[PDB]
Amino acid sequence: MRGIEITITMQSDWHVGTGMGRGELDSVVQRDGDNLPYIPGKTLTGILRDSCEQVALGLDNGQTRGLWHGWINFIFGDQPALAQGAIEPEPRPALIAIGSAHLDPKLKAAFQGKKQLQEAIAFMKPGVAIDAITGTAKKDFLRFEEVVRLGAKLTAEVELNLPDNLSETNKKVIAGILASGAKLTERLGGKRRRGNGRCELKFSGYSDQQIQWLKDNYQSVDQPPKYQQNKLQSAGDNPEQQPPWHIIPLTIKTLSPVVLPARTVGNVVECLDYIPGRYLLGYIHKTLGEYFDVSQAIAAGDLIITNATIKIDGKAGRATPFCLFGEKLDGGLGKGKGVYNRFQESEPDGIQLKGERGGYVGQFEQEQRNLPNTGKINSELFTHNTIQDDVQRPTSDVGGVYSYEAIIAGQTFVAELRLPDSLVKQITSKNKNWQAQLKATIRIGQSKKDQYGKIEVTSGNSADLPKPTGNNKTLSIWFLSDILLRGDRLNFNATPDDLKKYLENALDIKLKERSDNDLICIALRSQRTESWQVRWGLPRPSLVGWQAGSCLIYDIESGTVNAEKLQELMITGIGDRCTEGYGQIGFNDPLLSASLGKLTAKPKQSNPLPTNHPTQDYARLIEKAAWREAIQNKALALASSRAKREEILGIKIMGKDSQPTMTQLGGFRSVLKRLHSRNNRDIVTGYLTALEQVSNRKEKWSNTSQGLTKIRNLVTQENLIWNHLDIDFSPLTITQNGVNQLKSELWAEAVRTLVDAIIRGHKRDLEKAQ
Amino acid sequence: LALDNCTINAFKMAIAVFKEDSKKIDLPIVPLILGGDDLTVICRGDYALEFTREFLEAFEGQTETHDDIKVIAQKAFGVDRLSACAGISIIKPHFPFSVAYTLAERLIKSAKEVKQKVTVTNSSPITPFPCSAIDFHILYDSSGIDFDRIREKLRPEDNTELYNRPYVVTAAENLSQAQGYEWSQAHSLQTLADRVSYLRSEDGEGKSALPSSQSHALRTALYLEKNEADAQYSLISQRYKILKNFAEDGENKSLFHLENGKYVTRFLDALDAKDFFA
Amino acid sequence: MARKVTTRWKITGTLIAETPLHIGGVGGDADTDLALAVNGAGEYYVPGTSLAGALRGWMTQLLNNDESQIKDLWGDHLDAKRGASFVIVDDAVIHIPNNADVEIREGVGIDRHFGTAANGFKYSRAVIPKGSKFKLPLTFDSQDDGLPNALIQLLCALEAGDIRLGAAKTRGLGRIKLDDLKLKSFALDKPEGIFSALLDQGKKLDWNQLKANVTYQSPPYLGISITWNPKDPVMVKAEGDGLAIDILPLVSQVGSDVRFVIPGSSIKGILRTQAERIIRTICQSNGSEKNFLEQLRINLVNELFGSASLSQKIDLGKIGALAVNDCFSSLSMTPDQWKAVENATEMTGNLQPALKQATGYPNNISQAYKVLQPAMHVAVDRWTGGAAEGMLYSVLEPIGVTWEPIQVHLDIARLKNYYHGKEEKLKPAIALLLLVLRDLANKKIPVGYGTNRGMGTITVSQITLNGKALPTELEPLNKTMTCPNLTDLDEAFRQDLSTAWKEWIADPIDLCQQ
């Protein structure tokens, strides 16, 4: 069940901490991949759960354990971190999955490219401590804090995956509790207890009637039904595998951040920079298990799903060969120069090289004239905490802080689903449009119910089968993915002569290691992998092998290398566990074959809101704030020039004197503060005409540049203030007709800001001359 | 052996920088490697620059004192001293140290570029002049966690870099003959430590010589077009005269100077390192 | 479990600004240097933090700094057993009343040697006008039954209007009062309560029952009420010249109406001036050579009137224990009526209707001009006689405007902290204050504009001294005085203070140093 949405309206200024400051700011707010403020889904679930537990207290008569706490554990999942002792029941997952609440998509789009607006959404709030004795600001307790302007309307997807067997009665219970939590929730984020972050939270399609049903029925409920795993069901239908291999490219785009545990270590999880093929198998079930016995195919090895690597050159990127070495100072693929394929090239004279390790290289060919294109994955370390629910702060007993590396949004990946014709015949004969049905959005990774894990999947058209170049002199091997091999006693191990035996047997040839003193034969690194059987709630056995990008080369000692057998192994992969993406391999690739030392790398708007759009009122606040600061800056820029003060008002310095005397400016300045609104131009015009009538006061403004007329113009001509300031307001506006709406709005303040700036700036230059 | 002795001795000298904690049982530092060419320690973060500077200065001085060095260093380079580069990663306590050290390796690899930028006069083969260098980063939560992403985020305009690194640590007199001396002075660590010192200065009522709000506007301006950032400096320096010290053009109208055809500034570092000196 | 609340209390009503208010932002919607805090929608508002700390500050005085009690209401990050605050204070937007807007006060420093505006010591504070309203935004979660007795005291203190908020608390501003107090209760430990919170908006509770359960425990303070009238015209100059009349009285909004005003800062300043003058006179000290700031910093006035925060290798700054209220005219006007005076152009013409209106005698010019009387002044050239060219100017003298009694409010408790509890050492500062008041009642202290030019001299008819919870040796202060020489106070008490005063004169140490 999808398309339930939470809506949030912030009714006071609000703050979601990064848990740190930056520079002059002691607190700064979390911003999404579009640099706007947003509420992380992990916060949102945490707050909503907390209010639901308040309801559970009210229904369990304050018993901290009971039937209704049972329901909350049912709805929001158990907290096996905090329960302790010999708890026997498996920890249940939540039924409810909640995204991050983002700003409205149109408002978000409007800010694109408009950096100064993206800043103006926040503003600084001060804070201070007072010494109880002296009753003054306690120095070195002065604090400046970023907060986000109120009135923001945010929304997040919710998904419920209620059990299909769930009683209709229990659905209204769950709707009752969830509705109640939204109603009872009042605040989120930082300094809740001091008035930041007051909000309304509502579910689409839940209303008081849902609470009314609970209030009428709640005494009749029971404990929630016990949880059940969704087991597999094999069937044995699969027609036995026959060539050709079809190859379906799947494109994956990270719509949200994704967490892909490389190695857990205490309270922090490091992330990969590719998507393991194992993550997609659930999606294979959810979209193809109606057409063939997916589970039988895996056990037979009739299916392979590769890893997803970053897309480069329109295709799957390839992990950088460890045969490449860069000049320790000046070179390597990171610097676009000085890269040596040590299978073919000597080290340069004197210069020490270092082997390449990270990153991905795109396409290469027998003479590219350029180093292959290099890909990179952007990643960020997100941070979270646990609240100890009674003292309502983190504590070391509750585990404090934890953090995840994530792949950020907008990164894009490619993987290949590889199927024998045997299954494709079955699938196609049942549905010719199946490749259209592969288009889906799914959740994968760690923490997948919350803000993490949203990815788009999209089939391309069928790719061509790879066509390795046969070469009866030499076999050369590139590990495109991690390679797992059993030792001769079925244990895992990593000994390269096992792989020597393996390949020569599989290709039905004999191999000899490259013996040359200055061309390296072998460049491998070990690999070890943490993993979990989610089917069984236990870790997987620690896989050990060679990591992707390891490479090695051999001379062929005897036999002939069949080009067709090479193709087969490149499609199927070698070693163990190939089905989930390991074992992927490339033979005689031109990149391992060519010499590259001479080469280098190659050289390397927005639209308005409709006036009727609901967030237009919120955008109006951002527009005014950004305009105000820009006006203040540009007025102060123009006040800085002694020619500009003469141009605009005719004030100038002549010898020791100012024209007019400072008192005459001060008099005018005192009147100008009555110019609150454009109709008040009466008052300023009234003053100037009363001034002009008194000859002695009129001539006080002689030796100005026409000053009395210049002031009259600036106060009267609606355009003239904007002509002087000369601000391109286009990057500072986003509302339809916002420019005219805001110019007519701010006119009175623009005048006050400009004249005040000029008079003040003029005074400084008078002091220099005086 | 002499190099190990120099390393240990310079460490004893440098740990004096932990002055504020000198009242209590143990200094907030842990050596983990302390010999060969290598120092590797964890320490209190805001101390690390001053600690590491004094280590490098003491290390260069110490290396001159040994005959076991002198005859080799003099023939290898023409100076009594050797030198060392350092990389400093500054992290929150829960930040995974594996990631932080990984960045420190990339940072020192950057700092070692002084080997390329500074060379022995008429050297043949061209060979690095002895000159200690620092690179560092402060891993704010949105600043990413890999060196390339970090530096990329600090290149908002394609022709512009908001950082100016590595910092040369060796004093000018010890470099004064070298080819690239003038480059080494532009990149001298002293330039940053001076400018941070300015931001820590106060006006008579006890408030810093630049207010925090103004600093925030300056950081914002650096992400704008050069002409906008150059404008913003003019506006604020006309009020807060101290910023006259921070201009880099030599025309007192830009925080930027032209460098290898790019525009770069040290000023941003003075904002972000504002607290991180002992 | 989520924090096991037994009873949530919602506690709400109207807070009214009994004086103007200022809460500083970092830039604000005002053009000023000292600019108001505003919410993200630019509306004038009270930040929840600033109000919460104001309340917690007063609670600290009540509990005598017993932090082990405070931290169980307001929370603590350090104690493993405490954490989050049980009181909650939301933000409240300020409803400035109809037809009213932010006022700007002017502020100036007077060089104690020359008696004139000290170079650079000028400022222009924005203020919320008196009578603006905002919601009391409290919520409280009780983990045990009833309502904490100290929290009951706090609400009484708000109904008494004893808690000051925002900036400038010593010097005119920041007083607030609570009305319309409603308590809503929610028995969140039990089903009827939780559903009432979700749907039925709580059980009403009457305030009067809980108020009867406790005596309001006001902290030690001395009230000083001065009853006075202008003898010569008294005004503070409006911060901008008129068209018809050059010099106009200052006015402030007071709810619906405008009233003439003397800001507390002006009464504080003239009192501080005479206090300083007396001290330096006794010591034969000098200020001719000190800069303005060094002139301010002298003994006893430092403790009474306070000193700027100035960190020295220790902080010399401390809040002034003496506070003064704004004083308003008994007369009032509608806002447009006063605008008719400000916008008048002819002293013989449209001004006269506006003054007849504004004084409330539309029928009778003579009664209007017995209240507000315009007047002309000229500078006479010493050779020619007659007006020096351009030196013709005019004043709207408020000759007949009646004024309310000035309230001066002395925090005895805050002085006791500055003297480390040595209540005997209160005597000289109290003695000085009575000397300041003695000179004031003797007309020696002028107030407002034009003090050397036929304005500002005031009669005092009555001083009322009202000490609550005084130390017993100060009990004779509870008195009403009508003798300018204060002989209505007991001679033995005046002799006691005179002894302690002469003893301090003989060795004028920095008495606040223990």
Image (cartoon, coloured by chain):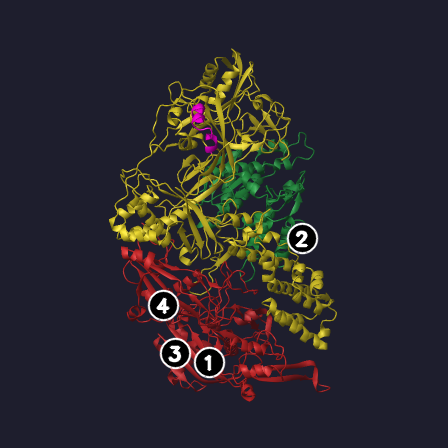
Distance between mark 3 and mark 4 Cα atoms: 28 Å
Q: Are marks 2 and 1 in contact (CB under 8 Å)?
A: no
Q: Are marks 4 and 1 in contact (CB under 8 Å)?
A: no
Is C476 displayed left or right of B137 in the figure? left
Residue A364 or B41: which is nearer the viewer? A364
Query: Viewer-proximal residue, A735 or B153?
Result: A735
What is the magenta range?
Answer: A423-438
Q: Quadrant of the C terminus of chain A?
A: bottom right
What amino acid is at disc 3?
Answer: Asn
Q: Main secondary structure of the magenta part?
A: helix
Q: Is residue A198 above or below residue B68?
A: below
Is residue A366 left or right of A60 when viewed as pictured? right
Chain for mark 1?
C
Q: Chain of mark 4?
A: C
Q: Which color has been applied to chain C in this rendered view?
A: red
Q: Residue A371 location, x and y as percent? A: 61, 29
Q: Nearer the viewer, residue B259 or A241?
A: A241
**Callout 4 crowding tier (Cα within 10 Å): few <14, some 14–19, many ≥20:** some
Residue furthest top in the image: A558
Q: Contact, CB < 8 Å: mark 3 with mark 4?
A: no
Q: Which residue is mark 3?
A: C466
Residues flagged by tags 1 and 3 on a common chain: yes
Which residue position is annotated with label 4? C181
Residue wearing tag 2: B252
User: Alpha carbon of mark 2 to alpha carbon of mark 3: how far?
Assistant: 63 Å
Disc with the residue nearer the chain's start (3 vs 4): 4
Where, by quadrant of the figure, is residue C363 drawn? bottom right
**Neighbourhood count class around disc 1 (C-alpha, 10 Å): few under 14, some 14–19, many 20 upward:** some
Query: Chain A appears what colour?
Result: yellow
In the rendered structure, which disc, 4 or 1, sits on the residue that comes first in sequence?
A: 4
**Cα–Cα gap, marks 1 and 3:** 18 Å
Q: Which dot, 4 or 1, sits closer to the camera?
A: 4
